[PDB]
Image (cartoon, coloured by chain):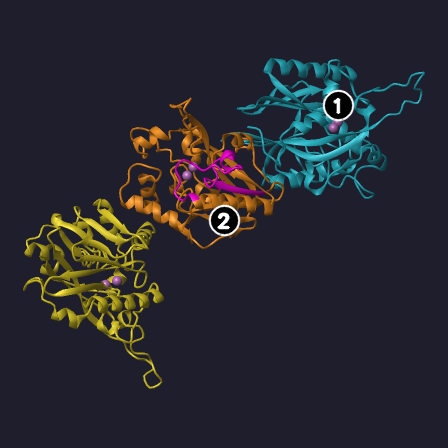
Chain colours: A orange, B cyan, C yellow
Amino acid sequence: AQPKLYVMDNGRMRMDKNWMIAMHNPATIANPNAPTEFIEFPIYTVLIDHPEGKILFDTSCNPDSMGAQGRWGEATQSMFPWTASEECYLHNRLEQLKVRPEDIKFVIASHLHLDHAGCLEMFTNATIIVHEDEFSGALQTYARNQTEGAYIWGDIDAWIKNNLNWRTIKRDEDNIVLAEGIKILNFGSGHAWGMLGLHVQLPEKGGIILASDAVYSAESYGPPIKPPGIIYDSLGFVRSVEKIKRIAKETNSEVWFGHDSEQFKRFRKSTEGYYE
Amino acid sequence: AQPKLYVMDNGRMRMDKNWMIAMHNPATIANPNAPTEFIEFPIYTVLIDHPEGKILFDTSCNPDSMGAQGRWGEATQSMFPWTASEECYLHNRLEQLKVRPEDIKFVIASHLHLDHAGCLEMFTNATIIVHEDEFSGALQTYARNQTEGAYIWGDIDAWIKNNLNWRTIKRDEDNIVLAEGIKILNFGSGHAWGMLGLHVQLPEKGGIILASDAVYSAESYGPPIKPPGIIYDSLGFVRSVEKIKRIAKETNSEVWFGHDSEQFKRFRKSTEGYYE
Amino acid sequence: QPKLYVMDNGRMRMDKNWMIAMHNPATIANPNAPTEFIEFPIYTVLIDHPEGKILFDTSCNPDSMGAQGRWGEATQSMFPWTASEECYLHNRLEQLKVRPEDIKFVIASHLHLDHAGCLEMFTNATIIVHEDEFSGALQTYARNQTEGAYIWGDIDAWIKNNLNWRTIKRDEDNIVLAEGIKILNFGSGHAWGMLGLHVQLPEKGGIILASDAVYSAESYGPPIKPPGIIYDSLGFVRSVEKIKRIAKETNSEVWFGHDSEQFKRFRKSTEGYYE
Ligand SMILES: [Co+2]
Ligand SMILES: [Co+2]
Ligand SMILES: [Co+2]
Ligand SMILES: [Co+2]
Ligand SMILES: [Co+2]
Ligand SMILES: [Co+2]
């Protein structure tokens, strides 16, 4: 048995382009009221069907995110609307691959934002792997009863109700081997409090770095590096992009970005196949 | 549950181009000794993982075909050499999809030539679907202990020893529905004594006709139609190509040829995915 | 100016080794050395200050003990809390004619069962806690841990009651809350993040509320004697040294977390207050 890697399409989000690429079109004396753009980008997840056990990188958005009775706050829904047909929901993408959520051994939470941790609550047999400081930060938003923003109260509530098995990656812990050719990369603070990536070595495809929101897009990645409009730790963000570039070169790996529309079009998706 | 169709690469064969396209390069006064060429073409099989049960179309060549102790006769090996790495063997292609031979419900033997019926002996639980006249003709070769040619004595011997569950399609029987969107096409005599094809209707991809050796290649298909060298029933061969064209037009189906190098290159193979 | 009250919130018992590590080691003459089950006070301190009332610690929740109690049964068997109704914090404050709604700041020295038990009462105050203590306690909650020093049911109630939190940052110290009231950040030691309070009273002078940064006079020494089970042993020692330094530089008295003999000497809220 050999691994197969799947890219699952979990719909699309839109938002002010400045969130993705800070100051992408600044006002000038000639164009003082420069309008921004409302860009569309993909939300996706990666399943590695590995002989040692199934590994899921990220979990997309909860199906109960949007709408008047949705878990996401109304301002959040207005600034980051998520559009997804039933087929796009992670539970349906998995069902079409005949993969039971009960058979997922590990889930890597790159971070705990609304569009990456939305379906953690499905995976009650998995070890949920997360950066310790990201876990702390998200839990504080919950304890403070925050109803708006990128950390979703109702999602966190469900994680606790469902008694998930958590494994926290310590801030000083890196290059954590989970299975043959599967290694967690600890990027630390930058985009959020604590970012994790994944390096996957496939027999045929070779090396892949799942960067998630440590690098939103090829435009972010550069050079030159272009940071996002809201950033927790700007210096850490730059260091993390530099680290990813270094690992990519040393290991001859492709870097898969968090939300790059053009790159995502190129992926073979789970409705067509997989990477071996 | 939805069907997934897989194209499995079972290696390459070479042979005189005149076998594929009769009289492709006739001698002339200026070129009286016109040399032929030794072309290479693919051997492949198709698995339809259908919710009603797995269906296999053709079975490629037996792994014990070639070599001094192989089942194929010496002269046959010299004229139709098959080259295949271990990974190309059908049992290995199926195992990499986690499909056991015992899981196959139907095998369609398009005909009983060495490169389509080579692995029937693996499928001891399946119903083996074959044209009655093709079955009769192959069995007579066996009874005559024929050691050379396209019908392999050792393969046939193994089918009998393994007591396969044959269903013969009668010469006047056509359009045999096996499962939702899976229909057997009876082309009758032409390339061989009795040729079967399959029409597959997939939700997304639409209609596919699996022609096997009723149409070797796009060059065979034309227009103009170009018949193969060595042909059992030349009138039936033409009738069958015209039947395939008619069905393809009426159902808006793509025709997948038996041995077309360029078409085969375009297929998504089982190492990369499937058609839905 | 301000009045300071010491409120008696009952008594707890536990293995002495929890308080003083290796207090009575086995020897060849005494290979099966027995320990003892010591008793100590749980208490809280109210400072009635003109700029707003400040409460240091909150004792145990009235619903802690019993078959239906919030504390886990192993926890109740190892750290049993005994308290009459009049010992409950809500009753101690009622006797002082202080409304819980009138507490401006509550200082959570840390989030252990016997200090954070009644945070949920104070839905109008700012609850002040070390950021790393808050994080740690919240992780135990998210993991649904029902035994130990961090009480799942208490935490559940802080969240359900929508308390107003102010986290003291890891590198933040000497935080003036009011004239003569300063938060002392001791950091990691006994727990993930310990806070103390320096109180300057007009007549009594300086008081340092150490809570569990220093359990007792025997802990404080010299020589310093650390507790059994300790988060950060180096930090624990550094914090005791810090307290000794501040006490000497400010001429302040150090009030320990759980010292039976010291607690007996305090003027209790039922008799009067400090000025
Ligand atoms: Co993000
Ligand atoms: Co994102
Ligand atoms: Co043939
Ligand atoms: Co053939
Ligand atoms: Co304590
Ligand atoms: Co204590």
Q: Residues within 10 Å of mark 1 (few under 14, many from 20)?
A: many
Residue C164 badge: none
Quadrant of the image containing the N terminus of chain C? bottom left
The rendered magenta stretch, by its main secondary structure, is classed as loop
CA gap, disc 2 and disc 1? 59 Å
Q: Does the stretch in magenta take in A218?
A: yes
Residue found at x 41% / y 31%: A18
Dot label at residue B193: 1
Q: Is label 1 in a helix, a strand or a loop?
A: loop
Q: Residue furthest bottom?
A: C29
Q: Which residue is mark 2?
A: A184
Chain for disc number 2: A
Residue bounds of the magenta highlight: A207-234
Look at 40% across and 33% down and name the residue there. A19
Rendering quarter of residue C117: bottom left
- Amino acid type at mark 2: Ile
Image quadrant assignment for residue C25? bottom left
The quadrant of the image that shows the C terminus of chain C is bottom left
Q: Where ligand 1 lies, by image quadrant?
A: top left
Q: Name the residue at the front extreme.
A: A29
Within-10-Å neighbours for mark 2: few <14, some 14–19, many 20+:
many
Query: Is residue B51 visible to us here?
Result: no
Q: Is residue B157 left or right of residue C125?
A: right
Q: Chain of mark 1?
A: B
